[PDB]
Amino acid sequence: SANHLPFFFGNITREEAEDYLVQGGMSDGLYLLRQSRNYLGGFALSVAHGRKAHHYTIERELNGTYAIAGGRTHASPADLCHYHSQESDGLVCLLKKPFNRPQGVQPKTGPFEDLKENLIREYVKQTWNLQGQALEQAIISQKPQLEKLIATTAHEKMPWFHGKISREESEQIVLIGSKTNGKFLIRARDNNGSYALCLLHEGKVLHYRIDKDKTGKLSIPEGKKFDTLWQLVEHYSYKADGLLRVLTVPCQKIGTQREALPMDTEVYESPYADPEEIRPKEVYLDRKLLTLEDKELGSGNFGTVKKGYYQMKKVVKTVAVKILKNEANDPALKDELLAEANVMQQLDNPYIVRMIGICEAESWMLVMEMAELGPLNKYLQQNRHVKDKNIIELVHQVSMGMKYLEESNFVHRDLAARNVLLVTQHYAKISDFGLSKALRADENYYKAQTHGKWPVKWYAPECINYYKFSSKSDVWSFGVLMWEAFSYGQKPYRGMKGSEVTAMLEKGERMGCPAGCPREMYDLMNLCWTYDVENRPGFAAVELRLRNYYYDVVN
Ligand SMILES: Nc1ncnc2c1ncn2[C@@H]1O[C@H](COP(=O)(O)OP(=O)(O)NP(=O)(O)O)[C@@H](O)[C@H]1O
Ligand SMILES: [Mg+2]
């Protein structure tokens, strides 16, 4: 633990950390330690330097040691802080003075904080009935939004809320069993916003009154005003204030739309998630069950896309249909195309455009999930109001879908913003994975310009030079895609030619940091753009680095 450290704050936010740093003066080398906001038992170090706050993720190693950016192992957070007081390996400056928790501030750790993870998990399971991987993938992407949502549930279902019990009943419930200091319950004093907070202190029960303001706010006599019992308990679990002590363990109760959340959409789960829905016996879909609309959604190098409708046993599924060119009809391409289509149909993840099946009719047809808001680059160019935090959320879902493709030994080959489609403004899906290989794309597609875009601008050096496509080269493309996202749909390597791009990269030169792009996101782009394939991270490391930054900045 880090609880004994007087400059350790527990699970506070990044902005609360920064507010403490300003409270302490903002002198260079002023620092504090806190908990990583990821349920991974890690830490975060917040440092003042040049009127700015610098945040670093401290991860727990398998052996129980600690390290920053896969670097030097340290025995404990205290040992890590001791080390960085004399040498800064990658840190902005050395650590000179700790900012101790102000008088009256305890670490934001404890039972209330501990319940959050199980509460979010339970909330997903009962709101969306998700299980296994669909459930895990929902929590990973949506943890910040889910944390906000559990804070709005009715206090009546909370373990520390005992309802209409009497003062004598509450006295007896708080006293029973081990007399842990801070053991508490909240009970209703009446139906009109009147409550009692019962707290255990040195074997005695303290009965505090919580009253509702004319303003609808809840507080104890002369104490801070809160909107909910959730906020009240959260604050009192680390700031004693009026109370003789912080709240600790709840007493056991007697007994024992273009803004929708990804899981609020039909496409989040596979159509065949319903056991009543019977999955086709192969990659082949029945042309008789498919109806296409006349108007095109768009087109590209490999074909034209239309909106369609696929008749299933218990519903009409809206689909997007890519009709391959005449070139795809060549008997020489058939086996490779069917082989890749089988592998594409195996992929099941919320953050990919699932390939439902194929139709060999008037032309070859790829039946896919609909992502109606269209491509990421065009959307951002048309909606510059989209916040940096919303962009982090979308690129993080892309990193999740890419980790899944990598785990599945699937190489995308054309990972770019044009191939990231939006279901909602908070829900991105990777499209056209492995299409260029399935269709045996020509040298003129890779080297030259097609539809106003230069595909080589997304290729790792070993792809252009040695034609070696791998999950590591997809990592490179992800860095270019991150740059596109942060540039609100701008084209990469402005006005350059493939020859000019290749030679620039050989020199170790890279694209610049987009306006308003965080330093840590530009550092991630630079890591993806590692020339050497062996030193370049895989998607597991990219997703975790992105996840950690996302959880630290969003709410
Ligand atoms: N599953 C889908 N759902 C909704 N719209 C889609 C889907 N797939 C493709 N589209 C639309 O069709 C447009 C063109 O798609 P596409 O044929 O893949 O070209 P591209 O990816 O922009 N360039 P290219 O590398 O040549 O394929 C996209 O920009 C979307 O508007
Ligand atoms: Mg595409």
Image (cartoon, rainbow, N blue to C red):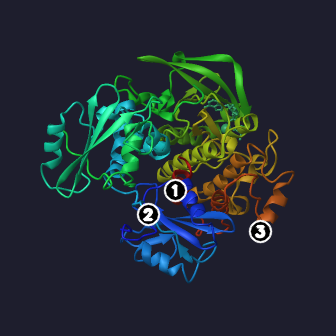
Q: Horizontal placement of 208 versus 468: left or right?
A: left
Instruction: Kindly identify which residue carries mark 1.
Output: 548
Between 140 and 209, the residue placed more toward the observer is: 209
**Residue 254 visible somewhere in the drawing:** no
Q: Which of the 4 image quarters holds residue 187?
A: top left
Q: Nearer the viewer, mark 2 or mark 1?
A: 2
Mark 3 falls on what kind of element?
helix
Residue depicted at x 47% and y 53%? 407
Q: What's the residue at 70%, 53% (across, down)? A: 517
Secondary structure at numbered mark 1: helix
User: Is ligand 1 closer than 8 angstroms to the Cβ of mark 3?
Assistant: no
Kindly tell me whether residue 500 is visible in this rendering: yes
The image quadrant of residue 6 is bottom left
Image height of 275 relative to 509, above or below:
above
515 and 493: which is toward the camera: 515
Ligand 1 visible in quadrant: top right
* Residue where numbered disc 3 is placed: 506
